[PDB]
Image (cartoon, rainbow, N blue to C red; front, side, top):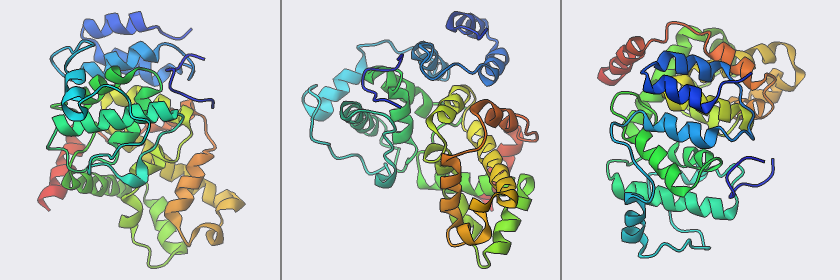
Amino acid sequence: EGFAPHVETSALRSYTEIQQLLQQGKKRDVKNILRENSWPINSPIRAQLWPMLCGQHQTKQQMLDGFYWEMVHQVFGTTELSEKPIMLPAFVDATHCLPYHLTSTGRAVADRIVNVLGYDCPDITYSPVLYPITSILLHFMSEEEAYICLAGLVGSKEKVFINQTKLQHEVTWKTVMQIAKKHTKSATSYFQRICPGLKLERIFMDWCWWILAGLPFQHLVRIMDCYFHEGIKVLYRVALVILNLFHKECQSNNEWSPDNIKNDIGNALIKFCKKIPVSPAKLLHAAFSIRGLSTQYISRIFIKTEML
């Protein structure tokens, strides 16, 4: 209906309002609008809203027909999109190059964007999340608009959006594990009881895939709306909610009885997320009900993990 042309088949505030608010420096009001406004997936607002949201985190505005195409020339020696899938940089996880609903053309575009980023950002050595986020952006905008969004997220100086090294990846999931220990202990305690010998680390290493490789597309998109404004803490909240919801479902639903899940709890989470029994709005509501997740508390437990 109202997507980008490289995509296949499956009162509410406006862009101008949000744009005016953001220019007046009112980010908290923009944050609350994003959390509470459920624009339909086929809405044309994200074509304009997402580039604006991603661009606020860098200080210099990037216009179209800019440096991106010069880098395409420098990397590929041509601007013609290859029809034979090209090799990706080593920072991607070949297991998780999630295309979602992109056509082969859209996937080729994502391949090119990811190579340009790698060329321009040599410090990125490990970032499995980067390709899926590229594909998602491309569902509502063109190539260069997607690259510009990503560069803004990757180049962010205060808010974290995308981890770029193995160390950053390790500290993050360790951090997600500690927070869950305080917020969702009943969930993990139960898992360890029906599956003796369970190493919770192997589970929490894939916390981001519950969201990016599990949740339905409409849930993902609403999450991205807030994530592009607030950063990775949005993903933390939803991770916690997923754990609590799955736990609640283990108590009353036969599909998630101990024998049906104990052999591989990690995969049970993924399968559960694919048919998540709540709507996007209810998912976000629980996610943003959670307290004690201040920037300062996360930052402190982050360095406590890093310092050991």
